[PDB]
Length: 50
Length: 50
Image 1 (cartoon, each protein chain N blue to C red):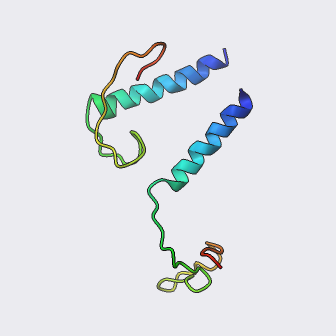
Image 2 (cartoon, one colour):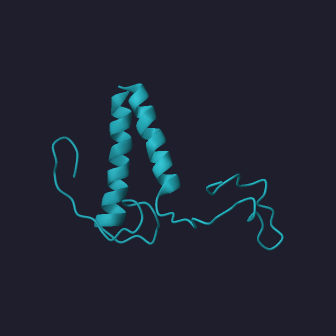
C-alpha cells in the first residue's frame, strides 16, 4: 500500500511525460530528460514504460 | 530500501543543482562578490583553488 503511492507518482510523471513530451510539444524547460532535450518516444517495458 | 530512496533523492537533488553548469576556473569569490550594487559576499561563499 506504500509502494502503490510511488507507482502512482511514477504514473502521474509518465502521464505528464506522455502528454507534454510525446503526445504534444511543451514550452517548459528542464522537465523532460535533463535539459538540452529534443523529444521522446515510448515503448512498453515490463511493468512500466521505457 | 528507505535509505536507498534517500540516496537517490539526494543524487537527483544534486544533479538538478549541477547539470549544465560550466564555470570560470579563475573565479575567486573573495575577489568577485559584487555586481551592480548587489551584495554577493553573504550569498555565495569561498570558491576557486586557493
